[PDB]
Image (cartoon, each protein chain N blue to C red):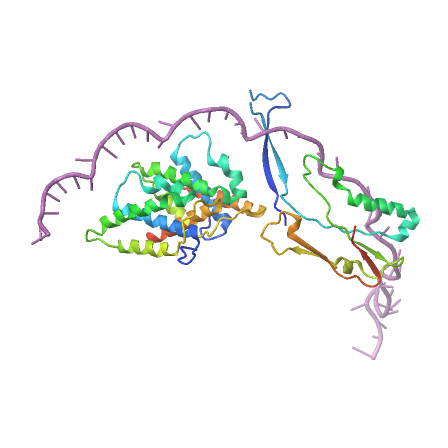
Length: 117
Length: 117
Length: 141
RNA sequence: GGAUUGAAACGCCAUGCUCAGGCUGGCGAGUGGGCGCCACUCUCCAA
C-alpha cells in the first residue's frame, strides 16, 4: 500500500492538499518557529470549511516568493494543488471521526511520497 | 520469533503504531503521572476508529517540543510513522477478539525492539 | 454473529475495611446491542400416553410460550420479547414426514434496506413455505 | 526317502452411559481552570 492517485475520497484529497501546502511553506520560510500545522492541524481536520480558504490564499505568497529566483520544482507544487482541487466538489462544514482518521491516512501517504527519490 | 517488518496484518500494524506513540510521549514529558496507555489502551483495541484521530494530534504536539530543541532524536519517530502507516488503508470500526489478541502481540513485539542497543 | 460490548462502572462506597483513605470502586458489564434467535422443539404422543399429558396442559403451554418474558424484567436482562410462533401438527399418531424437511420451510433473511448493522426486527424478513399433505401448518399463534 | 518328545490343533460365540438441572441477584467519571501580552503598505514616477 502507498499513495493512491485515484482514490477520489474527499478526506483523502484534503489530507493530500494539506501535506503539499505545509511542504510549500517549509520551502518558503526555512527554520520557522511556528508552522501552519502547529497552528491549524486540529481545526483543519475537524472543520475544513472554516480555515481552508485562507490557507489557500496565503499559499500564493510562498509560491510567489520561491519562483522569483532561479529555483523551481514551484510550478510542480502549484500543478499538484490545481489537479487536486479540481476533483474536490466542496469543503464540508464538519466531518465524522472515521473521516478524520482517513484524513490523517491521506496526509501521511502524501507526505511520504514527497521525500522519495 | 521477533518483530517482523513485513507481516502487514492490520491489527499487527496498529499494535506497533500504539507502542511508538507511547514512546514518543514518554520522551516528550518525563515522569508523567498518567500516560496514554492508562487512558486509552482499553478503548483503542476495541474500536480503533474512535480514538486514533485523537492520539495523532498529541503525537504532533509532542514532536513539536523535541524538534524545537537541539535534541535530534527529532525526525526518527516521523520516519517510523511514515513506514508503518504506509501499509494501512483504513481504520476498522470494530474488531473481533482474536484480532485484539493479535493487536496486543504486535504491540509487545514492537516495544521490545525500541529498547535494544 | 454478535459483537459484545464491555462497559465500565463506578461506585461511591466500599463494603469492608479497605484503607483507601471519594471515589472508591469500579465495576464492569457486558451487553449485546442486538440479536435474533431461533429455537426448535418436539412433542411425542406415546410418552404422553404414559404420563397422562393432556390437552389443557398443551393450551397452558402455548400460553406460557407466548407470554414468557413479561414477568422476567431485571437489571441485566434489558428488553426481550417474542415475535413469531409456528406449529406443525401431524395427522396421525406417528409422523408423516421427517422433521428436518419441515424446519426447512421457514427462512429468514435481511430486508431490502439491509444498511449494514441490524438494530430492529424490521431489518429482517420471514417467510414460510407449503407443507406436505400429511401435515397441518398453523401460524397465527 | 524311517523316526527334528516330531507329525494334526480358532479365544470363540453377544450386550444403550442412561434418565435432568436459572450466573444469578446491583453499583454517579466525578469534582474545576483567561490564547494571552503588541507591531505604518510605505517610500515617486506628462495625457
